[PDB]
Length: 190
Image (cartoon, rainbow, N blue to C red; front, top):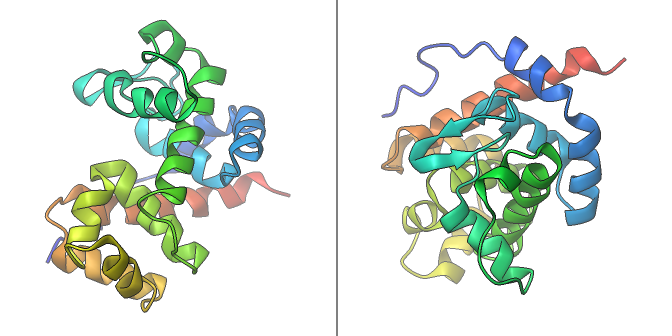
């Protein structure tokens, strides 16, 4: 169904800009047990490495995180009242910390129990894009059964499932863009 490779996405310059933040991605990723390569890919795809980014519904900063939803979710999990400010989300360090936190919330929460780390990666970017609920309900109304079904697929099969069945066109497209970004990041390791 979704023609998710059209138009081509050229990752080179988004990735070069995102790579300048790799020191922070590495630190925050370690701190949250999140993959720095996935953080960097998300930065490239979301802000293209611009820490002053503004997006969809005033999502802000390098990872284009929304204060009142995702940001709040991170503060809740931290036992903090409230939610981040706009100026906190424009701070690269704070932005990437919170985005890593949010990725950890998804991995250890709705997506808990996915055993293939590559399928987990794909599920994480689909869930970051359009929410874990929309993804899981393409499998089952029951979380546990959804996860069980996800665990029977490999990564190619999971993409094909998302491409045929997810209602959001952005969902398979985020997997395509993730792989364009991971390929482009290879040029920066010697």
